[PDB]
Amino acid sequence: GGYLVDPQTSETIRGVLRSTASLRQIASVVNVEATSFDVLVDKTDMGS
Amino acid sequence: ALNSAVAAEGGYLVDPQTSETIRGVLRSTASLRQIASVVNVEATSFDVLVDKTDMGSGWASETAALSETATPQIDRITIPLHELAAMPKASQRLLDDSAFDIETWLANRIADKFARAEAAAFISGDGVDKPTGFLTKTKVANGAWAWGSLGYVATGAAGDFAAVNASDAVVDLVYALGAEYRANASFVMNSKTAGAVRKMKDADGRFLWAEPARLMGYPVLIAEDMPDIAANAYAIAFGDFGNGYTIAERPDLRVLRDPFSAKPHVLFYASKRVGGDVSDFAAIKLLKFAA
Amino acid sequence: GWASETAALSETATPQIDRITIPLHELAAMPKASQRLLDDSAFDIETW
Image (cartoon, rainbow over the protein chains, first blue to last red):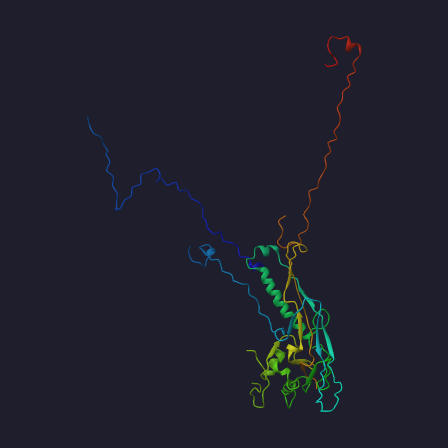
């Protein structure tokens, strides 16, 4: 009778869990539809 | 997620589908139950009542004063109606973890085993706790035929059929069976006797006999429990078994599961009860190979 | 024990019981006080 026992197969197959802390939640994310993105910064300030 | 052959690269996800219903070797169901008189009976014993004789007629004259005439004397045949019991032992871990319906599979397999095991008792069974088959009924040669016995015709030579006139030991067996019984009559043989019958041929090599595998227009039950062609054996029978042999039974299969005696096992106790012997001694003739 | 799927399955054991008796003794005291120094003292020794 041991041939007809047929174990179950754990309906959702799992994996090893890896951390998802990814620096996207602290940095600034910009949607871009081009080949490249720029920023325009100010390396100096004005005068008085 | 790679090729399905090697185990670690996705071979453990391949889950071989089992069959729908557990199959088995399909053993013989040609059991003489389909040709005889099967009678439901809720009792200990069944009593057929046959007429072993008949009456007399007068052709009474105009002025004769008609006297008495005969009146048929009557025989009672007691079917013993024994039981047939099988008790397989099945484990509780199997019955809980064995997704096939194991209980109805055992109820089918026990039923097949019983329908096959009663076929041996219907043909060659003795008296002790089993039905007496028609081979064990004190065979007396035909012509000197009494009611308390079965008739036979003999073939000639001891081991086999007759030398000069082979295969008419069959035809006089047919035409020595009674003109009303041949309306629905049948041969009963086993397979290696029917093969030896089919191997018979004329003086030129062609088979002289020409899915149910009937012989001379009469159907043949290929049993598996008659004797083969031995020195004084009764390998071939012929007759109207629907009148000749009476099967008495209960048409159900009593199962009791037993979780108590064998403790981690389930131990199905199944027993149907079945009996029967010959009711009409004229309706079965035999072929003896003696002389 | 875990039952070997195939086994005789004999009886395991039974918790052996035990009666512990609390014999319920008595604790008594007999101060023998004189009849003089119970009715000639100013302090009620009989209640003290």
